[PDB]
Amino acid sequence: SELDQLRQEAEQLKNQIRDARKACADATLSQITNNIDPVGRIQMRTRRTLRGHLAKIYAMHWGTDSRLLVSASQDGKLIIWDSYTTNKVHAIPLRSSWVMTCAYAPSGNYVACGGLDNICSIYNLKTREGNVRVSRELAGHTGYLSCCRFLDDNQIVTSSGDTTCALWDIETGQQTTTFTGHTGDVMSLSLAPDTRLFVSGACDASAKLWDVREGMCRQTFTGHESDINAICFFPNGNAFATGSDDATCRLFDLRADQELMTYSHDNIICGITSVSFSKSGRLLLAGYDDFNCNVWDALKADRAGVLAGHDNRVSCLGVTDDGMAVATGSWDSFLKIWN
Amino acid sequence: VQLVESGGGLVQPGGSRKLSCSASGFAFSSFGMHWVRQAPEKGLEWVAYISSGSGTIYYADTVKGRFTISRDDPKNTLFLQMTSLRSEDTAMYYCVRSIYYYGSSPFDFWGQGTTLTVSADIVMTQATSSVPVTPGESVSISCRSSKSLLHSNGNTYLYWFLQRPGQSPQLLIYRMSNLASGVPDRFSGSGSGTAFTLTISRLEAEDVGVYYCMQHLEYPLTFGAGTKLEL
Amino acid sequence: TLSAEDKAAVERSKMIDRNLREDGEKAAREVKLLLLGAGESGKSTIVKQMKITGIVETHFTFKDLHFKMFDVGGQRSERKKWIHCFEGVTAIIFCVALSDYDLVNRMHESMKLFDSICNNKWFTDTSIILFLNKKDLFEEKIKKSPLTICYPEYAGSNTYEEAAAYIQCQFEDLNKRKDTKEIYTHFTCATDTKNVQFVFDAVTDVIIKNNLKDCGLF
Amino acid sequence: ASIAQARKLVEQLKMEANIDRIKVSKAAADLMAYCEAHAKEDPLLTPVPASENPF
Amino acid sequence: GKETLIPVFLILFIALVGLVGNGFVLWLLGFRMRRNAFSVYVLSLAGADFLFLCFQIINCLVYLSNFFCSISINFPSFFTTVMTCAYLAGLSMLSTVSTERCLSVLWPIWYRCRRPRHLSAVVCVLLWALSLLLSILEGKFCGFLFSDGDSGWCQTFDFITAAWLIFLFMVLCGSSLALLVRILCGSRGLPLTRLYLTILLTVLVFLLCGLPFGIQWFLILWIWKDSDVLFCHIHPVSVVLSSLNSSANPIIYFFVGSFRKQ
Ligand SMILES: CC(C)CCC[C@@H](C)[C@H]1CC[C@H]2[C@@H]3CC=C4C[C@@H](O)CC[C@]4(C)[C@H]3CC[C@]12C
């Protein structure tokens, strides 16, 4: 039997993995940051309220100019908002109302969205005809889209329900790189700040660090109990934090290859739908489904503050690139911008 | 895209005439439309404006009461009903599309023009009426505003246009700093409150024509008299 | 006080608001229906009765009422990660092949699917229409093959009516919260016309309950 | 076959074995130094006065 | 004297409670909360109740002022007619809410699909206009404006408002009865016990607290002609019941309906 001794080799190699990353944990991040003074109480007010959607929204994404944000919902619309004046600059009708993710291009020329229809449709905002229209539809991916993210105007990575992330080329319309290796279906995705590599999170309770060029998984990060729903890099690009159904946020390091800190409390038992970091990375913002957001001190693992404006599940959140504001969207059809 | 003017000709004074602008190739109901005329040896003069959905209509004060702007969205046609035509209404009339959201570029496309012959504002001052221009050399023109165009939101509502001889004008620089689409990066705009500069570094051929600067801070919109570039 | 372009951006946003309000009034008056059930259980038969790559949309109108039917069984993943997208559906059309009682425990996994959907937290008030498909092939199959091989605890006659009523009592005894939701059960053949009438009669009670909820009467 | 998936899996763990790892204390000090070095330019962390925020 | 003073404290307390309730309802439905087609009726009823309750606060406050301080604040005589307009518009909104519920239950398909979007607004405007028409024309002929009018032609037009009030009650009772018959005959998923409890509660509230002030003020006062007995005993109680009804209306209609999930 080649088969049984092949898992004997795999179990020995995974034991070598656990021993190697056990040998690097000399002192935890709690022991390093006892000297650091805490952040104090973070109290953020609702500066804006974007009330245009008529159903549950599932995603938002900030633009790179920190003023335009897109938000997608189940009434077949994704609306681009002026965050400063609460103006709707576009309302794009969708071919399928079931949309679970949306993304904004870093150039600002494109938005992408996709859901249960298996297709990440890409919309051209800067048309000479004056209306937005479908640029390309990216099909052949056999599962619900969980997160689309642009690398530039031509590269886009998706994550699916068929346990598979894929890098696409928009002009040819064909997927160029296929990222397989996850066992349950991938739910979230986060690009690194240089966009040279990315992480994805699945229902394996496992996060995997990928590589865009060579196309193969480098590191695999375990430690969660239930399914991880959200993931986000630290702004250095050397760390990332995940969120799951455990009421735990855990952050990992790409160099140290393991856990660094767990963000949990006894009062919180519900799942985590969205994570993001601040601009300095000092505080991470987790969006829950006990209807509010918790501000976690990312170094000292303390609850800095609560963002409690929503009356349903906080489904999506994101921080601006200049770090001024936090917009949180939720299943009560309202976007709120916090500062 | 295509905007086609129709309905000109010789009109007896005191008479009436309806001008028509038939749109083609763009989503016409999402666009605010303007009429801008040009007296046959003079500069550009703004006439009227109708918004999207016909909810906001402005006129110039020289034509207020006499002119009626109206649009018909299902057949994509812009109208200008003009009554009691005077001899100062001998001009060539352009219909202009313009859309206003964050980051939009209004006054971007202009119609070809119809020619009709009749038998407290912000004053924009072009500094020179004509400059001698050598090809290849850099040139830089300027105009000045009577009021500071820098609004409190950070925007400066200064638009630059170029009219080639025998052609419609086209947008070069919108909102003092931003290049229009299809315009080369030789053109550059710069300025401050009420003092503005359009720079054409490394001038090529077919940059030759009359250049107009326009404010869009308040209605009515006022142009300059035009700076002519001559070889 | 705004500028001119800020004013035109405001009236553009107000026209976008009027379009969104009009489309929401369009979408709020349409009945959404969720098709569930296993493959080869007469799902496509029910789609051909209402009419004549992840999610399949079906639009049909009947007695001046617009229906959208979402066949979602074409795409296969973990169902718990997207079944909350279908809360707020008007009704769930579940369908079970009656002739799959002997084939392979296929009736038992169909019961497990109905047990998972019917006691889900997102469908705690949704009324479930339970079609029972291929009753004629069931009635030739029960005279030759017994129904005790599906149900070891069954004792009853091998006629159509008592055995079909036994399968009805099982499927209506899957649910826990009897008070909250209603289950409408119908016996359908391949060639019958009354199924879109039965769906309409089941939808009208949900329409009455939401018409009371819109008028604050609960 | 099922043996090919197991060869793919042990090849992936053989790739993941050869990773140059650093200490957890060094990586914690690097995240600490990034948090201290950019703390003056974080407007969520340090509340900014109402003139220069746009909200 | 003293026998009138003890009802008046109840008037001011109940009027203040209904005042803050109606103000909260007005602010929420106007600005904070999304409005249904039905929410317009609740907003209009809160608006109609506001004027009436504010005028009750005025009419009890100046009774306190006249009794203790004796300032003798004589009033403009057109406060009574706009108070009457507020009262009649509130009762019309109650009956129209009942008819809208009956129309929703009887014809669900029409109510979802073919119902016009501004029908609630146009019905509210027409009932407010008719209430104002019946108010000022009762005001001018009976002296509650600038000119004074004859008492003989006053009672001809006042009985019209009483007949309209009885019709407005019979419309509420007739429409709530048809809904009960429909939900008790062939309705399945509805919560029947809570439903007839709240319908019957609205019917007794509208009959026992909404009606008696109008009945006594218009039809009852003229016919009886028993002045010594009627004003001292009957009138203080009539205002209180009607005042009480306005206070309980936001709680019954909006707050139970909205804040039940909280
Ligand atoms: C014809 C005249 C007497 C009517 C004016 C009555 C005045 C006092 C007020 C009281 C409350 C107001 C209503 C309050 C709510 C709304 C809902 C809005 O979406 C349409 C207008 C409408 C329906 C208002 C109409 C005018 C109104 C009824």
Image (tube, coloured by chain):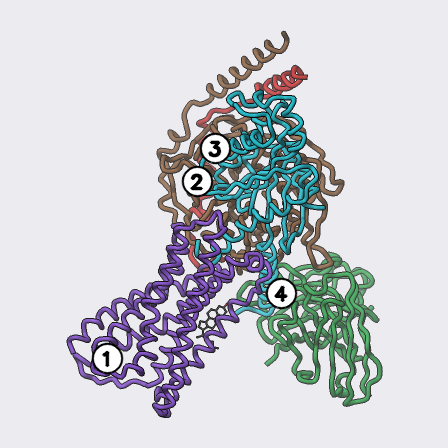
What amino acid is at disc 4?
Gly
Instruction: For ligand 1, tell me if the residue under mark 3 lies within 8 Å.
Output: no
The colour of chain A is: brown
| Tags 1 and 2 touching, CB below 8 Å | no
The colour of chain C is: cyan
Tell me, for residue B191, which label it has, or none.
4
Q: Position of residue C169 (x, y in %)?
A: 51, 33
Given this view, does label 1 or label 4 mark the residue nearer the observer? 1
Q: Position of residue C137 (x, y in %)?
A: 67, 30
| Tags 2 and 3 touching, CB below 8 Å | no
Q: Say which residue label 3 marks.
A: A251
Given this view, does label 2 or label 3 mark the residue nearer the observer? 3
| Mark 4 to mark 3 CA distance (whole Å) | 48 Å
Instruction: For ligand 1, tell me if the residue under mark 2 lies within 8 Å.
Output: no
- Which chain is displayed in red in the rendered image? D
- Which chain is displayed in green in the rendered image? B
Tag 1, which secondary structure? helix
